[PDB]
Structures are given as structure tokens and as C-alpha cells.
Image (spheres, rainbow, N blue to C red):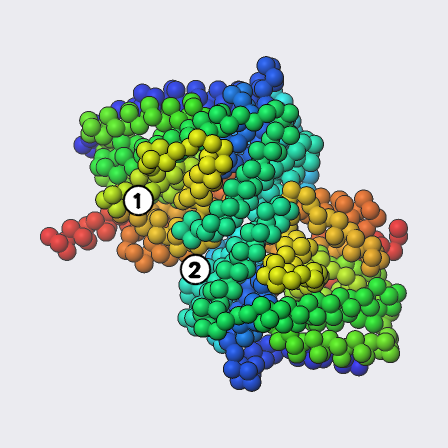
Amino acid sequence: ANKYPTEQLKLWGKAKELREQYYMNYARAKEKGGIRWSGSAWALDAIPAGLGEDVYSLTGEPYAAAVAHDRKFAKECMDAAEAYGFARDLCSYMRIYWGGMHLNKYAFGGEFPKPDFVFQTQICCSHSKWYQHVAKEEKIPEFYLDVGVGPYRDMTDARLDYVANQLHDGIAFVEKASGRKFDDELFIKAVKNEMRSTSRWADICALNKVKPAPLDEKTMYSLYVLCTLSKSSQWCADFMDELYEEVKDRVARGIAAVPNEAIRLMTDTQPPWSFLKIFRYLETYGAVSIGSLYTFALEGIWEDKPDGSWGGRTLPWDKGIEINDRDTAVRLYADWNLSKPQWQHFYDPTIKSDMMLRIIKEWQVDGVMLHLNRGCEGLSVGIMENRLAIAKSGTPVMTFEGNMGDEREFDEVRTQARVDAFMEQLGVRRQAASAWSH
Amino acid sequence: SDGLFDQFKTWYEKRHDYARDWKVRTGGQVVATMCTYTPEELLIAAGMLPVRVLGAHEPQNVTEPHIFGMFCPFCRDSLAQGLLGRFDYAEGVTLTQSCIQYRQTFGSWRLHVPTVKWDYYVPMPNEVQSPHARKAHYEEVQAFRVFLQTLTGKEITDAMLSDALAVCDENRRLLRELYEYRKAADPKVTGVEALYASLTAQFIDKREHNEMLKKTLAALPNRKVERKTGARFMTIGSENDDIAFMGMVESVGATIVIDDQCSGSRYFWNASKPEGDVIKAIAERYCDRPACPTKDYPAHTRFDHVLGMAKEYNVEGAIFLQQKFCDPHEGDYPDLKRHLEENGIPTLFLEFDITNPIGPFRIRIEAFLETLSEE
Ligand SMILES: CC(C)(COP(=O)(O)OP(=O)(O)OC[C@H]1O[C@@H](n2cnc3c(N)ncnc32)[C@H](O)[C@@H]1OP(=O)(O)O)[C@@H](O)C(=O)NCCC(=O)NCCSC(=O)C1=CCCC=C1
Ligand code: SF4
């Protein structure tokens, strides 16, 4: 039954329109002599932003996720990549992207738009292989930022130097690849907007700690995506600020995403994009997903707050730190990105275990549903150790197997039955707890 | 017949007995090492025996709670060896960063193998092509040295590091000298014999291994060859450490004359450069080594390395042995295949689990040999 007031998000249409405009801008970039580039959502996109306000990216994973939402087109793309000769168990986003390039079809209409260069971050092994194939097929320059310097908590001066010095190489690379002169003012503005957008996304997620949750994770998938498109843009930073104001007002008014909220769930990585209806099904039980380390920190950037809680990282200028020159901005930009929570499990899965346990506590989670995602080695490494750590903690936890991009490795019927069994389990545990504490 | 390589075969079969007895003789610690990028010079200088974790190629169920089955058989087989207690004599465990899947073996091992007393993860740069990687790795190697000095309470001096580097470089040079014999029309060293030698290099005391390599090379000039060469094959892959499988290949009418794999050439290929700062010499040797696919970007330098080896050893056919789910090698495979075929080398693809019936692979090898016999 509906205990809480509920309301649709007012900025929904704007969130959808900003994403559509991003994809249309990439395709139309050349009409007015713009620059186009491609790389991961984890690329350090403020660097190409130093080349102008008409520099448009296509981030590889969000594009592939958009394709995966169209089951037929995703299958066609994967079939083209397989025809070239790639193993079907490679990253499903990478296979999709490759296939769509060979088919020469853009998901939003027209030919697959050729990027002027590749600007990539490498932490997952597939990060290089993805764009090595692309750069060869498109005959374009390619640059890779190796961020593999170990956990942020162990960072040394020399590790940060390695990343910072590579970024200086990246500046020289984008100047040469584009023929344009890099502008320090535009670069610094872009670093600052990326700091704003990623910290503010974390601030928004932190508002979900309250009961009732003002946002449900399925809705959040249309909001966390903006930082995966252009976190260093003014439009993304400004929209995050606007969205924060709306979510604050929902909290202030007691607004629930799910009016019958009785169960709070946490997920993990990469949901199967053509099967988001599972979230609506869970709503019928009064279950809301409050998020995941993935939704919160694929791009969100976090810090420990004065009360020990997790919140958006403090912007350097609110801490008395000046950013008035290229070299300072590069080193602060490298440090900001190296603190990304979703990079840490590449080195030490217990860091992610502890992060998940902390989310469970601070977001008042009743149960955890973990996707064993066969489509993504990078976000799945360590997943079984994370499951074990949650299991030892006493929080109910279940797994389901799937693949975020390739429906052939996702069993809708079995997964729904596993989730329904989990809702039953959570009800039984509540009955037992009530009976024991009277 | 002549049993020249029997010592290497014994060392392989009895690797664990060897390590236990090594501890009795020297009083040193044993360190389980993962991935061939481990800076073993540092461990030797610290008085320890590096022993590379490898799988057993037998059925195992102990890793299912620790590593999801979308990951490769090698990383699971390897972890199972620790969970089953087979490395209980190793006080340390260390991994130098490359493939992300292997990092799970290390993570689960340090958390759950109860005989581990210390662990260390070396974040070696992946982008060895970057002008900044050698400085970064210099500092990583130095930091590991400081760690080991702190752990053992004994200063690890430059002289100690230089002596360990000399031992490792001699091993690398001796293994390359052994490989030279494989270029002959009737090789005096089979691919199986080369594999026993190059794999055992990774878990036998290098001083003892070098002595055995020197004896082997002293015997090769006059060693009698009885078998026919058959087709000249190259094996390509990640680890490729199933010697029993390689023995089948060489029994059907072929010789494996060279390889691109971490059981073999990719481990030892280059010795360090002469250099007065021993940390730089060590760090740069690993950065300059033929690259793991994970470390091979932006350029696929591996393609030139593999093709150059194929031409220098007169390869007639190349066999890709791939672990199921192996992303770094899967990412390189379609275009490395094309590069070899465009340069006149037909290729064969075989995929492996932890265990595999040999019958199906032999049928494929025999059919591949029939193809070579036509063009
Ligand atoms: C487009 C999408 C796939 C589907 O969207 P939708 O499901 O929302 O469908 P829709 O057709 O657009 O709209 C219909 C819905 O709108 C709802 N509604 C209406 N008015 C509403 C209101 N006022 N407020 C709220 N809601 C309102 C209606 O209820 C209706 O929903 P319903 O039928 O269930 O009732 C969306 O989930 C998305 O963008 N995901 C992100 C994908 C991506 O790119 N991710 C980044 C990947 S990067 C990555 O993985 C890595 C990076 C690096 C390293 C490794 C990994
Ligand atoms: S496997 Fe995952 S982390 Fe790696 S390239 Fe694919 S989407 Fe990115």
C-alpha cells in the first residue's frame, strides 16, 4: 500500500534531451568544423576540451549501452564483430561498438561518424584492444592514459607523476592530432566542471540515504549517464546542480520514488539494459533499489565527510587550493580521477568489499542483488570475493548471472524467479526478526 | 633416449619437493610468484627462492566461491593450487601487474591461503611504450626493494642486486643459447625439451638451473638426433604450460621450433642492458621485454616480435593455443592471425579448459599437417 507521497521527476525531459543532444552533436560535429573524438566514459575528457567548445566525444560504453537497449541492432552489431573474427566472450560493449563501426551505422541515424582521434584511459585490459582495432580501421591517431598505479590510498609522488606526465603528453597529442592550439583557460574550466559534475553526482546519490528514497535506481540510470557522456562540460555540471536542487526538494517534502517502499535494495554492476523491467517488477513488492557502487561511483567522486559519512568530494577551491595554471590543473585532475571508487577493485577487491558494506550501512539497505556480469571483465573482477564479504556481514545477498550487453547470456525467466525467491527470503527474515525481538 | 633433459623433467614433476629441500639446504624463504613480470632479482637478492605459481591441469572445484567462472582456466587452476595447500611452504606471495584476471588469483590467494606471511603487488606500468614508464617502474622496483629490506631486516645492497641480476641475465642468455639449436634443420632440442628448461627456470634456484643449462649446452654439439623433424611449428599463447599437450603435437609429425608464450620465450627473451644503476637496469629489463598483450599499446609491437621469431626459426605453421575467456590474447588474435597468414604462415586455433581430452586436439593437429603439405 502507498504510505509515502510520490511524484515524477520534473527534470526528466531535460535529462533525456541533454543525452539526445550529445549524440546528435557528435554526428553533426563537422557541419561547422568541429572536432570529434572517441574513448571511454573514463577518458579524461577535459584534455580534448582544451581544444575548443566545439569538441564532441562519443564515449564507447554509454554508446554501446544505448545500442544494447535495441536488442535487434545489438545482435546485428555483435554478429558483424563475430564475422570479423573476434571471440564472442569478449566485452559485449566492445563487440557491439566494433560491429556497429563495420556496419557503418549510428544508433541515432546515419553513418557511423568517424572520430578524428582516440583519447582513451587504460585500466581494463580491453581498454587498449577496443581502440587499437578502431584506430586501425578508421586510420586515426590514438592516445592511451595508463592509470594503473595501484590503489588511491597507497598513492606515492612518483605514481602521481607518472599519470600527470602522461597527461602532458596527451595535451601535445591532441594538439597534433587536431591541428589546434590547446587553450589553458578552456582546459582549466573543463577540469573545474568535471570536478563539479562528479562531486555533485555523488551529492545527489547521498540524498538517497533517507527513507523513503527520493530516487529509484532505474530512474537514476537516466541521470548518472550524463557524466558518462561529458563530465567536463558546463552543461553536465550545471544540470547536476539543477538536479541536486530537485532531489533536495523531494527529500524536504518526504517524496518517495516508490510510494509503497518497504524494502531497500542495493545492486552492483552493469544491469542488463534490455531488461530494466525487473526493477518495476520489484516495485510491486515495495522494493526500491537505492543504487549501487556502479551507479554512485562509475563517475561520481567521493570523500569522507566530517561525520564519517560518504559524500561528494570537496572542490579544491572550497579548500583554499588555487587552480590557475596548466601544471597545477593537470596534477589536480590526475589526482581527482585516481580517487575514483570504481577503479580501486582493479587492484584490491577488499576495497570494493568495504565500499559495498559502507553503502549498505549508510543507505540503510535490506538486501543485495549482485549481477555476475559475463559481459564485462573490468567491473566483474573480484565479484565473488565481494559476495563473500557481504555474506559474512549478515546482510542478505543473492546473485544472478547475466551479460549487460548480450541478451544471449541472460535468462530472464530464471533471473526473475531468483529475485522473487529473494523477496520471499527478505519477508521471512523480517518475520523471524519481529518474532525474536517481539 | 639419451635422457639429457631428465633433470629438468624431474624438477618439473617434483617442483614442490625441490622447494622444501631448498629451504632445508639454504635456510631461505620461498615466494610464490605470479606473472612473469615479477622482478625476481629483488627476491633472489633478499635470499629467497621465487617459484612461479602454475596450474595442475586437473579437475578442481575449490575456486568457485572465489573466482567467477567467466574468468580463464589458468587463473582458477593457479588459485586452486594455493587453496589446496600445495604451496604451503611459501611464506610470500607477489604479483607484478598485467592481466586483470590474474590479479584475482593474487587477491584471493593472499586473503585465503593461511600460510601466507606477506604479500606485495607491484603496479608495473602497462604502457611500456610511454616515455614515462621506465621512471615509474624504477620507483616501483626501488619501493619493492625497500619493502623487502624492511621485511627481512637485512640491507639489500647494490652489490647484492647486481649479483642477482647477473644470475638472472646468465639464465636468460643460456636459455637463448639453448633456443639457437632449434633453428637447425634437425633440431638437437625438441620443443618439449625447451619447455621443460624454460618452465623450470621459473621455480628452480637460478644458480642451480644455470649449471644444468651449461651442462646441457656442453652436451648438445655431439648429441645424436634420431627423430625426424616433420613440420616446423610455432606455439603462441599466454602461458602454454601443458607439456603433455606439446608432447602430442611433436608425436604426430612435427617439431615445435619456437614459441611466443610465458612458459617460454616471453619470460626470458631479453637480458638487461649494461648499466651502472642496478635499479634502472632491473626495471628497464622488464619494460623492454617483449610485451604481454595487456602492455602492448598503442602499437602492436608483439606482431613484429612474433613474425620475426617465426622467420628466424623457419616456422611453417603457427598454432594459437588460447585459454578460454582470455581477453588480452583474444583482443590481439584476429589481427595477429592475419599478420602471420599474410606473411605466408598458415595458422591453427585451439582453445583450452583446465583439463581437456587430447583426442579432439590431435585430430585437429593432424588435419593442420595435411594442409601444410599442400602449399
Ligand atoms: C535510455 C535507457 C537505456 C532506457 O531509459 P528508460 O527505461 O527510462 O526508457 P525510456 O524509453 O527512455 O523512458 C520510458 C520511462 O520513462 C519513465 N518516465 C517517464 N516520465 C518520467 C519522469 N517525469 N520521471 C521519471 N521517470 C519517468 C517511464 O516510467 C518509463 O519507464 P517504465 O516503462 O519502466 O515505466 C536509460 O536507462 C539510460 O539512459 N541508461 C544509461 C545507459 C548508459 O549509457 N549507461 C552508461 C554506461 S557506461 C559503463 O557502463 C561503463 C563506463 C566505463 C567503464 C565500464 C562501464
Ligand atoms: S570489460 Fe568492462 S571495463 Fe573492460 S572495456 Fe568492457 S565495459 Fe570497459
Residue occupying image coordinates x 57% and y 33%:
A171
**Which quarter of the picture shows residue A102?**
top right
Q: Secondary structure at mark 1?
A: strand
The relative height of residue A288 versus residue B214 in the rendered view (above or below) is above
On screen, residue B197 versus residue A315, left or right, reads right
**Which quarter of the picture shows residue A34?**
top right
Q: Amino acid at mark 1?
A: Asp
The relative height of residue B95 versus residue A57 in the rendered view (above or below) is below
Q: Residue furthest left?
A: A438
Q: Secondary structure at mark 2?
A: loop
On screen, residue A246 versus residue B329, left or right, reads left
Q: Chain of mark 2?
A: B
Residue underneath mark 1: A304
Residue underneath mark 2: B65
Q: Residue B326 or A203: which is nearer the viewer?
A: A203
Q: Amino acid at mark 2?
A: Pro
On screen, residue B67 versus residue A143, left or right, reads left
The nearer-to-camera label among 2 and 1 is 1
Density class for disc 1 (Cα within 10 Å; few <14, some 14-19, many ≥20) is few
Residue occupying image coordinates x 59% and y 61%:
B279
Percent of width and height locating residue A30 = 61, 18
The answer to whether the residue labelled 2 contacts the one labelled 1, judged by CB atoms less than 8 Å apart, is: no
- The reply to whether residue B143 is visible in this rendering is yes
Q: Chain of mark 1?
A: A
Q: Residue A24 or B362: which is nearer the viewer?
A: A24
Q: Quadrant of the N terminus of chain A?
A: top left
Residue occupying image coordinates x 60% and y 31%:
A174
On screen, residue A166 versus residue A155, left or right, reads right
- Number of residue marks: 2
